[PDB]
Amino acid sequence: PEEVISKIMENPDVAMAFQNPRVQAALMECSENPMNIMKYQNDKEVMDVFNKISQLFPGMTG
């Protein structure tokens, strides 16, 4: 996934957050389906990240 990881370097905030377990778990779990966020909803950390990812990537370029 070096392709997408390269674009994350755009916001050092997500690249730094990418170094968090709840985030890597949110993305690894995202594989199941966007319904995974309904689980990290309590993880305020994943919220700021998943809310940033969608606020800046709403149409999802990838």
Image (cartoon, rainbow, N blue to C red):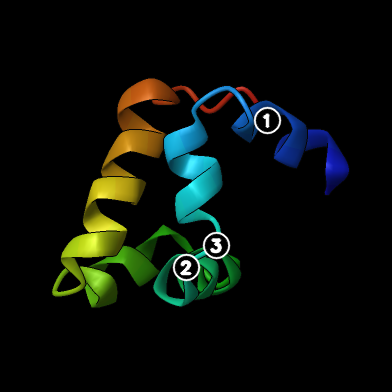
Point out which mark residue 20 bears.
Answer: 2
Q: Give percent across and percent down for residue 14.
A: 47, 42
Q: Residue at x 64, y 30 (%)?
A: 9
Placement of 24 over or under 51, stated as above or below? below
- Residue 16 in picture, x, y percent from top left: 50, 49
Separation (CA) of disc 1 from disc 2? 22 Å
- Residue designated by label 1: 62
In this rendering, would 6 be left or right of 55?
Answer: right
Mark 2 and mark 1 in contact (Cβ < 8 Å)? no
Amino acid marked by disc 1: Gly
* Residue 19: numbered disc: 3
User: In the image, 43: left or right of 62?
Assistant: left
Crowd class of label 3 (few under 14; some 14 to 19; many from 20; radius 10 Å): few
- In the rendered image, residue 47, in percent from the top left (x then y), is placed at 23, 55
Spatial distance from mark 3 to mark 1, Cα to Cα?
21 Å
Residue at 31% x, 64% y: name it: 37
Q: Earlier in the sequence, mark 3 or mark 1?
A: 3
Query: Which amino acid is tagged 3?
Result: Gln
